[PDB]
Image (cartoon, coloured by chain):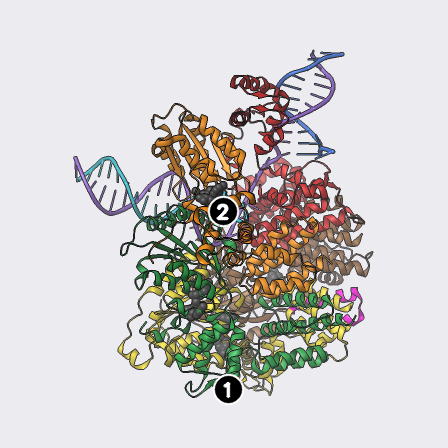
Chain colours: A red, B green, C brown, D orange, E yellow, F purple, G cyan, H blue
Amino acid sequence: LPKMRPFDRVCLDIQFRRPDANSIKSRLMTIAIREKFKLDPNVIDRLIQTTRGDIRQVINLLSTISTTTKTINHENINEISKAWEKNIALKPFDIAHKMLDGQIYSDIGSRNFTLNDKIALYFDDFDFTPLMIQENYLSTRPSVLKPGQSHLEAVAEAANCISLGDIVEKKIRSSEQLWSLLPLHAVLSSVYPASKVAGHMAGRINFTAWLGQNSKSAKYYRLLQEIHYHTRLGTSTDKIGLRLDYLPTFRKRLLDPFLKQGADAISSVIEVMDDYYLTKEDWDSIMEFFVGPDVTTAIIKKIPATVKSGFTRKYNSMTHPVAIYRT
Amino acid sequence: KRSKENLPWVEKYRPETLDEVYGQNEVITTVRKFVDEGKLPHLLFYGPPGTGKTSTIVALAREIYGKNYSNMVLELNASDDRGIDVVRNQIKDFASTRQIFSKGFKLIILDEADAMTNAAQNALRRVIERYTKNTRFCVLANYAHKLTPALLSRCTRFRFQPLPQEAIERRIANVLVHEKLKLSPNAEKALIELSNGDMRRVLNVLQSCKATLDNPDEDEISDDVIYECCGAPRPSDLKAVLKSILEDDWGTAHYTLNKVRSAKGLALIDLIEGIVKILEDYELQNEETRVHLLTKLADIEYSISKGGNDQIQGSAVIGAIKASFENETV
Amino acid sequence: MSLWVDKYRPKSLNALSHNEELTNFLKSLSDQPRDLPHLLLYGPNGTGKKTRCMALLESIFGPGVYRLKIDVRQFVTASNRKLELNVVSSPYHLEITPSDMGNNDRIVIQELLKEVAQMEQVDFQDSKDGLAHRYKCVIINEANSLTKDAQAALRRTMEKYSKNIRLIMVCDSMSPIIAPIKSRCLLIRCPAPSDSEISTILSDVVTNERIQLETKDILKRIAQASNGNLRVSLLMLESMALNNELALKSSSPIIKPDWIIVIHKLTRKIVKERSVNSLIECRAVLYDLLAHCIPANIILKELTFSLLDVETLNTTNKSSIIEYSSVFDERLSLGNKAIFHLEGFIAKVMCCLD
Amino acid sequence: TLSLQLPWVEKYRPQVLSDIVGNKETIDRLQQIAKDGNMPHMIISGMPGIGKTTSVHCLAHELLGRSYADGVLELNASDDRGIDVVRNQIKHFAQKKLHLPPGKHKIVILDEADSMTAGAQQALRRTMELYSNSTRFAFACNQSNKIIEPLQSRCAILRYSKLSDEDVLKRLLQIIKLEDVKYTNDGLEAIIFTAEGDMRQAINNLQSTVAGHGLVNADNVFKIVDSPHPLIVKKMLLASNLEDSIQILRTDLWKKGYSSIDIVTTSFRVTKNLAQVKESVRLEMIKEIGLTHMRILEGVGTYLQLASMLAKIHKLNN
Amino acid sequence: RKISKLAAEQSLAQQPWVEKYRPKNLDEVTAQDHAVTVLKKTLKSANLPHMLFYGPPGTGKTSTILALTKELYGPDLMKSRILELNASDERGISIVREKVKNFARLTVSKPSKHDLENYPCPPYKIIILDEADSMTADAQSALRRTMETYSGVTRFCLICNYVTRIIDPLASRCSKFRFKALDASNAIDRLRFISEQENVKCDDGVLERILDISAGDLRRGITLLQSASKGAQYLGDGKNITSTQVEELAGVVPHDILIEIVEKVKSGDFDEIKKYVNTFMKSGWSAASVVNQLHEYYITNDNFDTNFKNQISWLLFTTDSRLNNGTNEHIQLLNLLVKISQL
DNA sequence: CCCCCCCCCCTTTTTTCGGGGGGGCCGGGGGG
DNA sequence: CCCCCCGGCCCCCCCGGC
DNA sequence: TTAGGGGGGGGGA
Ligand SMILES: Nc1ncnc2c1ncn2[C@@H]1O[C@H](COP(=O)(O)OP(=O)(O)OP(O)(O)=S)[C@@H](O)[C@H]1O
Ligand SMILES: Nc1ncnc2c1ncn2[C@@H]1O[C@H](COP(=O)(O)OP(=O)(O)OP(O)(O)=S)[C@@H](O)[C@H]1O
Ligand SMILES: Nc1ncnc2c1ncn2[C@@H]1O[C@H](COP(=O)(O)OP(=O)(O)OP(O)(O)=S)[C@@H](O)[C@H]1O
Ligand SMILES: Nc1ncnc2c1ncn2[C@@H]1O[C@H](COP(=O)(O)OP(=O)(O)O)[C@@H](O)[C@H]1O
Ligand SMILES: [Mg+2]
Ligand SMILES: [Mg+2]
Ligand SMILES: [Mg+2]
């Protein structure tokens, strides 16, 4: 859980897993012979599966049933299991696995696992289910393709419905707070798109990558804003124009010279930086924006360490202008 | 608040007794029988705007208690705070305490309960049950989907229908007698047609019409006055526009629509609604015509609701009608 | 030093060199600026809208408009969050970009603009007429990015306090602007400069910067590749001069932005391979582009217009591509997560092409 | 008149476990527990108006007798049930010293426990375990899934199902015999049909019909209880021709005063559970209904929008 | 330093023409008689109802309500009798429950003898909720009983551009007034008066062309007239304003460019259309104006059949609806032109 | 003993208004 | 004159369909 | 029908 994040690497992590049937069979038999009721050993596994490994729940079930039903056997195991079946909400990975299974979308599966059940499965975690579906709807071998329909067509329909669900989600979380639309979102984001590509997972279920990418985008946008407002007094443009037009040109006057003139370009680069009230951190942030063929990590690393040390020494041994005076 | 004559007609003519509520004979008779026999249950009044729910409950409270009913009934509405805390303290003490003035039972009127939070509705569940021996609850609603099933299960439901024509005519006659006004038969028909079963609309339109007459004493309200004050299309305009669209060419239809709309500054939405109403009575050979008409006109209305270009919307209406009616041949 | 795009920017209305009719109209507006209405300047990006706005302000008030300072203003939301807005101000005007605060931009309209408008001008700012100025100018950059709530909040402010503030909003497209706001502004179209004018400006820059041009055809090629974007043209001329030792030859290649190269590679990948694995791979490219401050709308526009330029596609494919582009542009305008709509558009294009 | 007749739901509320209809096995288990004692922690879940609170109160009374006043702590949604209340009042009640019969324990009743906050539920966990030797907990709820898993692990589960028409008829006939109500078979059938398995609703409708019309027949019953609108919506959605669906919409729903939002919400709910129709067709219908609902929520709640929705639904099935 | 305060008349004399010529009394409203007469009769009836003014932009709703308040209460008593809340003020449910309700419950301010002798002074106050369509549904519902319970001392005026955004109960509680669009047939007199008072010299039909271009918005027409007057004065040539200058100032595409676009569409070649549109967007023409002009050209052309017009009407409607959502103009215009070329 | 099989359990985290709950200072009052 | 008590703003986190 | 991969623990040639 996020709230347990602080405990990441400060304690010895010990895990207790669901007890197996054999380890508790003897204790259950002892309790049964002590409490003076008849239980068939063969139905023990069914009871342990009913409670999902909860020994306390198993003992409570025994105590409750033994009040009137003095015999636990195959003649009544089904009813007991159904009545005392724990209803535990699935986790994102399990929700994604079950939603993207073609069996539940067949006629028999649909009559067994109904549309209401599918919608309820979404409500187990409504904040992560659409993200998991969007992440894992392209990694399946479908088993529900209509005759004459290819996998790509179903993928396109699912993507269109996902876009519509995104529009609905934007509507829900607005000032109007139209939460009554939540069920419709469930259909538009998880159920319908899954029904188009439902099948067998073609790999491993991955966690949504949209969250980390959004965080990275936010960080880069913050850096771009800081740089734009540092260079605002010298450039006539906005942040988008700065990123798309100005930065590539600045690349040829801030990093490229060091690759040609070696350590003799420090003066010119510092002069250019001062002309735009740019700092060393601004330099580093600028050099991280370029993408594709203009990636600079290797380029900057290949620069001799002496050149970088001299650049830092020269920058730190001078008085540079200030653009924004915080007071 | 100098006098009741300074109030708007919607508030000046608010019923004070159950005999002045029209168009709800079944509900009024049943509630009167319940009150007379002392068998009033928990009540729910579900209905559309301006049907007489608040007036009916206020009249019932006044009949049960009298002139001082306001000090004997706990009335709450959306304008007031009705959170779980209020339910836990104010309503609970009101229901569990005796009346200060008389020795009778206690009434709680939760008007506009559809705006109440789910937590407060859940809290009211046991309040309604525990103090049922001496307290009664009335819940007024316009939307039943906002009421929890548990609250609905504890109340007896009464549906307020849209006002019938006869009740509106009787109330109009009473208003005319009070105001010393003359209304034409066609004017009355037009006024009832545009009301959609809402008495507040009728009263507001009549008040506007009275202000339009140069001499309200010696002048009579005609259909022309009603159409002009509301700025609504006349039936003749709708018929002419539809006929031009259905039988004339594109240029003639466009000219007719623009001319009809510019003579009195008619609104496109009103014309669309009138044409839809007219076409609803048409006997069409193919269902495709009806499907296309309904879908395209609904889309045009939705687009108009957000603004857009009026000329393009009118051309779209004309083209949609013309294309939809082309399915009646083959 | 300062880039040529910034070193040679005009600082007056008489220094303008393209769209002489627009210059004449602006001069006519500045002749009697006391009754100047609110202005909305719309046109293609990179044409000189901001330069002309600054020139108009200089003509109305004088050169002092170019003495700029930057301050920070604090705001508190309903959730107690603290937001910072960078305000660029001069002795005569104030520049703001409310979209920096996203959905909170409304507050900037509600508090800062209201405070400025509810204050009359008391400093003796003597004008050309002999009497002091009575209003302060406010420049709302990127007005097209304002949320509808902020625009609604702007409505009554411009009317009640028109005697203390005059608004100049610069936008690239008027489609996102609500009709009530457009009704309250004088709309000024700003056409992009012609190729000949761009070539003249570039030749002037070359002459001032002592650049050896093998021929004047290079300037024409640069202007044609800029598609009317003067900022891009000047920055490309500077870029092309720093890669050829300050000497431009007829064989000098035109340098494209890195994101443009990535988008062209994506277009070629989409055209060549139409498969689910190809879509999965293209998702990585889309995420990578979106994570480096490349707007989704720009990505969609460039992808659509690069796919339409492929010579191996037929008319039906291009028609389907443009229809899907329109639909998914509407979806992007009405959505939050751009990657969803972009992936849907790419999937539909792949389906149609295959 | 300033007098009120006691509702039959309270006048005839069961006071012993033997007077509760439906869920025979669960009620028998409750009687067995009341006989032997050693009542365990339990959670009773089910749909409203089926006899959960009545069963809990009857069990508590049959178990505690004259000690009910001191041995029962009852809390519901109308009372404060925050974390502070759990940590102070419930703890004090559990720690209280009370001499009870040999095989009896104190009872804490938490009616409508599904409305409690997660903090209070978490706090109750150790209180239940440390004082189980003297106190036992009985929760009553409608949605058992809202109870945290740790609490469910410590309590038995008693799920209540809908009352069959036979049980409702039995109880209604008993009340009629105890009230000398004149009735007709069709009237009782209509009462059961409109009740939909809810005993409280059935009893309230019967009392209202008796007090308003006297004779309990189909006509009088339907004058008090209106036809369920979900069934009318289902008929509208299952109509063959578009004209029939539009007629149902206009005559039975729109002209009766039903709001557009209610109509669209009911249409969505009915379509979600229309097993006769294939799942894909229901999904397309749900998409269309969601578009119509979004249009309505924006302010356009016109009859034309509902007509267009019906036309689109019919086009989907063609 | 400090500057001497200006007089109200002097300040107004240097304001934009839209604010300078705002109606001062109910008689200055041009083409809203159907509602202005009803509002004027209330100055003697003294039974003003709850009002809901709705209509397109620039029709005179705010001006009408301000004039009504000024006539009812006068310059001095107006401030204590009017509570104005607009989109620039916080209008949540809490504000409605506390601020609006508290103001409504307050006793009416005591009129002075001069006010009673010179103005009707109705015995109630007015709450004006401008741009009420921006308020949430819950806040609107919170007003339902406040409107009715305290109607004796308070009246409510809701002004909106989209009537559908007002919840049904509030619309039912309010008497509705629709403000009609101002065109060349009902607003020519006001524009002519404004031009005459400003010594603006224009050729015949210039004012009508301005009003037709405005498309129901008188504020836009007045602003365009002011711009034309400023241009003419700057030129200082003494000649009359012409319709071509007005069209150039209004952003109307020249007819020749429209004919070129039509010819390109007729050709049907995708590449040529794409190239021409790419060149066209460089001029900054607004897509909405281009679509409107294309609609005017095609729908009113006799050289096209019925099916073509039926299809083009829906195409134009779809393009306009998509543009109204704030979409890229280039893509939408190219799609529309390509679709028309294939009809 | 390493090897085999089976079973269980882990991959990982963004946000527009309104209401309700829970914790923490603060300040008014009473009292010694 | 100063300490204890205990009600009253402020603040921050968590839901939101059925 | 078991998403892939790692951790636990009873059985055993
Ligand atoms: N049945 C009726 N008979 C006579 N006048 C009526 C009737 N119903 C409504 N009216 C008129 O409409 C006014 C408002 O009636 P209300 O009962 O307050 O409206 P409503 O039914 O409560 O609508 P909602 O649900 O509150 S939006 C009354 O003061 C009457 O003038
Ligand atoms: N099984 C039943 N047998 C007899 N009467 C019943 C039965 N169930 C309900 N009733 C009657 O309906 C009334 C209300 O039932 P309750 O059990 O108190 O409500 P409920 O079942 O708790 O519904 P919720 O979930 O609390 S809203 C009782 O007082 C009885 O009169
Ligand atoms: N009916 C009219 N008569 C005279 N001038 C008018 C009229 N309508 C608009 N105007 C002019 O337009 C200006 C603005 O009018 P407003 O009433 O503020 O616009 P509006 O009707 O409120 O549009 P919205 O809904 O606020 S966008 C006025 O100051 C007048 O100069
Ligand atoms: N009249 C002109 N003469 C020379 N250069 C110009 C002129 N107008 C604009 N520019 C150049 O074009 C570049 C971009 O202009 P910009 O102000 O960004 O226009 P917009 O505001 O439309 O984006 C500026 O850096 C400026 O140097
Ligand atoms: Mg009411
Ligand atoms: Mg109970
Ligand atoms: Mg206005």
Residue with the mark numbered 1:
E196
Chain under disc 2: D
Image quadrant where one finds the C terminus of chain B = bottom right
Which of discs 2 and 1 lies nearer the camera? The answer is: 2
Q: Are marks 2 and 1 in contact (CB under 8 Å)?
A: no
Viewer-side residue, H6 vs D271 = D271
Q: Are marks 2 and 1 on the same chain?
A: no
The answer to if B269 sits in the magenta stretch is no
* Image coords of residue G18 (percent x, y): 55, 48
Dot 2 alpha-carbon crowd within 10 angstroms: few under 14, some 14 to 19, many 20 or more:
some
Instruction: Find residue E185 and report its horizontal and vertical position in percent.
Output: 57, 84
Which is nearer the eye, B147 or C299? B147
Q: CA distance from mark 2 to mark 1?
A: 87 Å
Question: What kind of residue is marked 2?
Answer: Leu
Q: Nearer the viewer, residue H13 or D205?
A: D205
- Vertical order, C81 against E27 (above or below): above
**Disc 1: host chain:** E
